[PDB]
Image (spheres, helix red, strand yellow):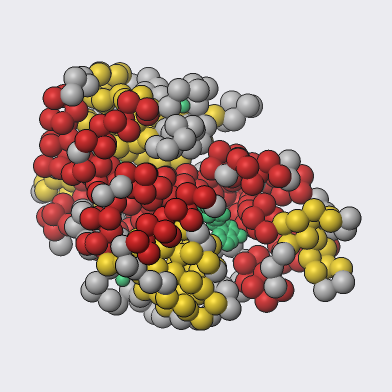
Length: 229
Length: 236
Ligand SMILES: Cc1ccc(Cc2cc(=O)n3c(c2C2CC2)SC[C@H]3C(=O)O)c2ccccc12
Ligand SMILES: Cc1ccc(Cc2cc(=O)n3c(c2C2CC2)SC[C@H]3C(=O)O)c2ccccc12
Ligand code: NA
Ligand code: NA
């Protein structure tokens, strides 16, 4: 995004520098009382919650460029006990204490609005995910995840649309009730495992079962959506 | 709500008058090419969608005071094909075209922050609902809906925590977001009643086992504590 590049310049102009993280690192964590604004510039992360018995809940995936805030902009207190875990091999992020951010959002309104609109994109993402699950259950969820991966990481090859992700990252994303759905899908030549990669061969099927996420992508990321429509 | 009362004052200072709506009216709709910022001041609404075959989907509930924006602040285009439907008898709202909300928030960062933090509360709300559904399924979803009803509208009495909402409105709200009046949800709710988690007495409803709701909606309970600590505190 150009809006993302301008935000990066704005931060680096104000002496906030990028930080590199490696896979499994927590950019912020649920036990930390200091809250942050993360500008995820590059890489893939997941928002988790860890219960007292140790079970890890995967709540949300984010890719750069995006903004993730662990605290409320006004109170500076936590919005939820969450970790931001790196799942790509490396990720680059700008890490801003929440108080320090208020100063900088204020001087510039273009950049205030860039962060505002990322929140709006998150809200409508969650509602669309929910709408697709209410209609089509787990098939909807899984079709939705494959759809966004196709739009974002897909590449045209003679074998279909290849999802061009490191095979290690694919494992981090989930690639017994899920086992059976992924089975039906290749069982119907919607997806295929060739060359140890992952190819989509019936993109219309994915659009059919994740209609509201498809609409979200159209409305919120139209230039990308347009590559495959 | 002090921050919201100040916002209302800021809108009237810039000449924006409130509008009144009635139950079943749409404050904004999915077909309108112009997108709006709604400052819901009083009353209860729901965000709805429609699928190809005409099925109404209830996505989200909102109560005054709150902000609901139908379009992106920068591009001014739709965030999704949604309607905002009034479900209380009446509702009062301020309706601002999206391009103007931008001037208004640029002129006063106190009010910018008020709206920004409204979005932050929505984001965290949806993640907590997701988490509770992941752990406890639809029972988690229903317990959380009743938990927030209790915190927001509940008043401690000798018979338990009375839900201070007319019986009409309050049965609709017992059904979490989804398809209206489903058999599965009606059974979950009546099971909670059979087990005396929420009970009918003298024309009113009383939550008598708040701990049970907290047990099955722990992440929405934490969300309310983090987002609305003074209201959470009153009943804990
Ligand atoms: C499988 C999958 C589904 C979902 C998202 C979320 C996403 C993706 C996305 O490309 N975008 C957004 C999100 C949601 C803000 C969160 S907001 C608009 C756009 C953007 O990034 O600018 C993924 C992100 C990373 C990796 C995998 C993901
Ligand atoms: C039963 C029930 C459960 C759930 C919500 C949602 C809610 C409620 C709520 O009280 N609040 C929020 C929400 C979700 C942002 C939307 S954000 C913080 C707080 C606030 O409004 O200030 C209700 C809203 C209206 C009526 C009933 C509701
Ligand atoms: Na934290
Ligand atoms: Na609209």
